[PDB]
Image (cartoon, rainbow, N blue to C red; front, side, top):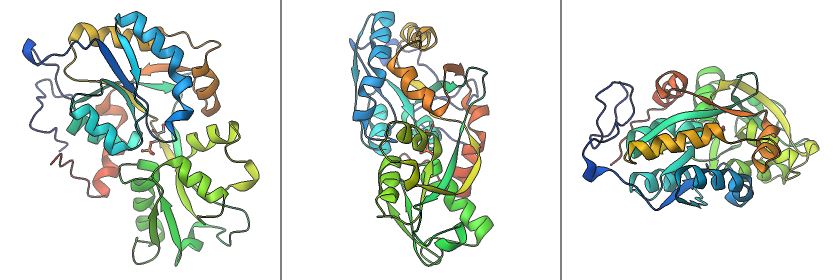
Length: 295
Ligand SMILES: O=P(O)(O)OC[C@@H](O)CO
């Protein structure tokens, strides 16, 4: 029963907003605005995407601008409002971005053999006194933001279903804003427990943002699709095809993109469909009562 906002049409039944055929509704911007997902300080990813965005500019013939958005809500609103044209949305926000911002997802990173994904992990710091999930009872649990799968919705569902633990009764929730804030907060002993994306954790460890001896894992979830990449529904069809081509034609070898994302096992972009690959996420959304009320 997934529903797009009534400002979009879904004539072909693939659950994503159709490209308009009224030419007055299409946009052909002279500057394409791109945003990666704020799982971490976007300053970390500015140079990571730089060469990729140069290739995108050459492929599309447009100027390209990196938008260092700081929260999921701001990123969703920017695409809904027409200011953001191409984005990677965090896994947990793809259904909301599809429904309320007209996001058309088409690709996801994968390993060289086509395997993909990340898991939620619940982490503490060594010596915290929190040595398994059950030890969280009566204490605080750090979440990232309410649109996060691994940072809020998946751990809330797992704790309620498998550990008989609900926020406000069995633990007190706190919100850090970002995976990196949660991971840093655990490493610095601000948080005794946090639910985080282990892909982000591994790249932060590789970049020496935190050290291995500062973090202990207490739980690892099932595997989820990673960040979904896509386009605002109302760019001209010709431009959308060129953007997709730019994603698949970019040569990763020797680039800052490969240097970063090889640290969570990625090597390429592969096609996905929202209907298939995000089914597990829509179910976790429904288990948390998510409505997709765009307001
Ligand atoms: O914050 P979540 O929703 O778990 O998304 C992280 C995911 O985008 C990592 O690839």
